[PDB]
Each structure stands twice: as structure tokens, then as C-alpha cells.
Image (cartoon, rainbow, N blue to C red):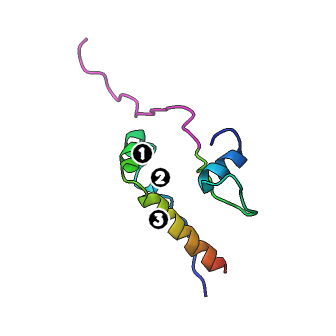
Amino acid sequence: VSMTKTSVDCTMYICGDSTECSNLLLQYGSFCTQLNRALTGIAVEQDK
Amino acid sequence: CALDPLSETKCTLKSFTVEKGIYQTSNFRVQPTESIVRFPNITNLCPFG
């Protein structure tokens, strides 16, 4: 019926506390925004 | 976008009006408070003496 509503943010996943890695990820435009929106949609649809 | 949680929600939704709900705005993070380096104690000093 449902699975664990895992919500992996990638700002901490791809990059640790490294701020230079955060900037390098920021070079990629909206990849992590799409990923997080997709995972939150997955979680909300699990609740639904 | 950093004055208050309402402002953070507004800047996340990109809209001046915020609908009734719970919106993820940012991420909480606990910075390391201090640094510790507990290396093993020197078993024997080199024989400079």
C-alpha cells in the first residue's frame, strides 16, 4: 500500500558540509529542486 | 527570505500569498561546536637524548 516516505535532500547527500561542493552543485540549475519536489510528491502520495 | 519563517515560505513558494499548509523551506543543520583530536599517546620518544 505504501513504502517509507524517504525524503533525501541532495544538498547534504552529494555534498557534505563542504561549501565549495555546495557552489558546484549550485552550478547545476534546478536538479536538486526537481529531485526534492519529486521525493516530497512521493511522500505525500504515500500518505495519500 | 531570511527575516522570519513566513518570509522563508514566501521565498520558497515564489509567491506573495502563501496557501494554508506545511511547506519545506530550508534544512536544519547543527554545526560542529568544537574540534577534538584524541591521537594515541606516544609510546616512546625517539632517542634524541
Q: Extreme bottom residue here?
A: A1
Q: Earlier in the sequence, mark 1 or mark 2?
A: 2
Q: Residue at x 61, y 78 (%)?
A: A45
Image spot of residue A25 (x, y percent): 38, 50
Q: Extreme left residue here?
A: B48
Q: Are marks 1 and 2 in contact (CB under 8 Å)?
A: no
Residue A12 numbered tag: 2
The quadrant of the rendering that contains the C terminus of chain A is: bottom right
Give how far apart the Cα atoms at labels 3 and 2 are.
13 Å
Please determine if labels 3 and 2 lie on a single subunit.
yes
Main SS, magenta region, reads loop
Q: Residue at x 54, y 31 (%)?
A: B34
Instruction: Tell me which chain the residue with mark 2 is part of.
Output: A
Can you say whether B33 is above or below A31 in the image?
A: above
Amino acid marked by disc 2: Met
Instruction: Tell me which chain the residue with mark 1 is part of.
Output: A
- Observer-side mark, 1 or 2, equals 1
Q: Residue at x 51, y 70 (%)?
A: A38
Give how far apart the Cα atoms at labels 1 and 3 are.
16 Å
Amino acid marked by disc 1: Ser
Give how far apart the Cα atoms at labels 1 and 2 are.
9 Å
* Residue at the disc numbered 3: A35
Residue A22 numbered tag: 1
Q: Earlier in the sequence, mark 3 or mark 2?
A: 2
Q: Extreme front residue here?
A: B16
Q: Residue at x 58, y 50 (%)?
A: B27
- Image check: A25 left or right of B28? left
Amino acid marked by disc 3: Leu
- Which portion, as a residue range, is magenta? B30-49
Residue A7, located in which quarter of the rendered image? bottom right
Residue B40, located in which quarter of the rendered image? top left
